[PDB]
Image (cartoon, rainbow, N blue to C red):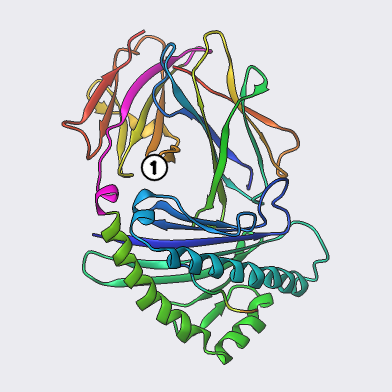
Amino acid sequence: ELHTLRYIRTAMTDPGPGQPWFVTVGYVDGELFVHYNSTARRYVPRTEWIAANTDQQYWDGQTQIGQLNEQINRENLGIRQRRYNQTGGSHTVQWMFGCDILEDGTIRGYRQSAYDGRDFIALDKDMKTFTAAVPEAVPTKRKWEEESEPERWKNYLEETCVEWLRRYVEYGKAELGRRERPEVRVWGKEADGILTLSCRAHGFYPRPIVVSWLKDGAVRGQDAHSGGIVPNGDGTYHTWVTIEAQPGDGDKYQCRVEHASLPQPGLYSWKL
Amino acid sequence: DLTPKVQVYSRFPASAGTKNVLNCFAAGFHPPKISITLMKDGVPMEGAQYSDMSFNDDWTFQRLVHADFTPSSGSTYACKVEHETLKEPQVYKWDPE
Amino acid sequence: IDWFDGKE
């Protein structure tokens, strides 16, 4: 199993040009499914399955949650800035929260905030208190615990968040469980006296994947360079791995690609 | 180091006269404000979904820009990136093959 | 579903 629901909020003083100062996007199992920003002023579906399995009051309510959060975040930006004796400039509040459903049936919850890209405050593991990462968050810690905020977030994370995640996973079961095969290409580059072999996987899903370079049978990917897993625009992923080879010895290298969508692991040589 | 880490790649392995999508992915940067322009021969391209940004667990931001296109022969494609952590615009060229 | 942020 292992499903996830995540919301991430960005509130910035300096978006900037033609960009919304406030944004919230939601992800299920690592895939964007809802979106809200201060320009649209509306929560909006980003997958067909969320749009198909909700009614108008879902979007109207979420929209208003976002509009209210938008105001709350406007104020909180001002408050944090003041705690930092900041008078202007680029500053950002980020929030991350959500829940995991592991394939035990066990649950996990997270709620943490950053300020200017650094930890500011977070609800701790037991969800009974908040932990200030910086002295500037101490007063907030105090106010929240005096207001029973930990209890409130514990409730959302363990009940509301989880219950809704179960619905989302149900709604997009087919989409989330689909498989798409990557088209693989190996390409050879030469600008110096060093041969750069590249292997790219295009449009694979799900996310997990293995791409490696072998030098006549032996993974010689101990010195292969990966650009990691990066996203396409259509809900699939891309990855590319290179390796430097002595001119000559180009016919000794093979890229091997393992992925859940494949009939068998792909194995590809370079040929000019 | 909070400079943008950029990768340029096509949705499908690029082919002669074949419709495709050009991608530019910038990650690991802060602040969130950033300029990412897809360009064809030193000039911007056409309809560009700059739309989608998020951030990782370490709080660093990421932004994907993608646009529909057909790779023209003899043309150079690249992703021009401008960001506060950089003195001057960075140009990441796209390798078609 | 998204949820209310707390007031700081």
Left or right: residue B36 versus residue B95 is: right
Residue A41 image point, x, y percent: 60, 59
Q: Residue furthest bottom?
A: A146
Q: Is residue A176 magenta?
A: yes
**What quarter of the picture does the N terminus of chain A occupy?**
bottom left
Q: Residue A43 in the image: x percent, y percent?
A: 52, 59
Q: Write the start and end of the magenta stretch as one range.
A: A173-194
Up the image or down, A125 lies above or below B58; here it is below
| Residue A267 quadrant | top left
Q: Position of residue B63 (x, y in %)?
A: 56, 44
Residue furthest out toward the left: A263
State the residue in front, A244 or A200.
Answer: A200
Which residue: 35% across, 20% down?
A: A186
| Whether residue A228 is visible | no
User: Is A93 in the magenta?
Assistant: no
User: Would residue B43 be found to the left or right of residue A149 on screen?
Assistant: right
